[PDB]
Length: 324
Ligand code: NA
Ligand SMILES: [Zn+2]
Image (cartoon, rainbow, N blue to C red; front, side):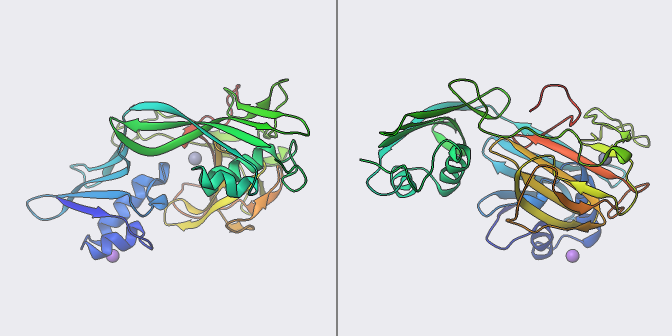
């Protein structure tokens, strides 16, 4: 058994290289990860656990994303690797981050415990209701956050549930609803809705829909199709289904060229097998904006766009009824 803690700069391929794992084995792991793409997002501090057999060959890899979540890659008799995801539901605690404006909101928010990303999420959500340049105080704020713990250990997982500002120029408050978007007290959403399709009408034919229980034709084992396939010719324009920011731009051996956009604290969308990517990391995009050209890169039986919608990092049927 090998315990490896991810450090700045590491990639799954780099870790395998330093731990002596063969290229062929790296490819089997990348192959099964096509349908999950968990290993591409490894961050410093997370841990990889490698289980070697009597022959000193990798028999199982455990990717500890957090103390309550792990992806398990197991070697099968046929040489391939199978995937299993395990999640433990610890306990969630509520924490209130309150402060007064004497520094600017950002400074005061950071001083009271909120992170940069939390401050960004807050300013993003409240941008139309608050001018963080003119509405300046004496004014205070209260942020309700839910933090997940495991026993006495903070998992690092958290989510802002409510945002309220006590302003002299008028109080403002927003709450995270069941649909993953923030609404004001009157029920007006502070975040824009999404388009259902990532392509033009001409290519909306679905050749293969979302199906987490899909069984492999050869082995009979469950190999989930975590996205929707659209019948696009190589070169067809691909558009973002929502406002957001490009957070991932990679060239994967199996998923081919792919992109991931973060729309808000809850939603993300993935676009795989692209022939060409027209945006870069950090770039903000609008709903309906062209972000790439469909392709046939990676591993596939034919050209097509594989589209995914993730809710709190869990894939869901992009064509499902309830979803903003
Ligand atoms: Na290698
Ligand atoms: Zn697909």
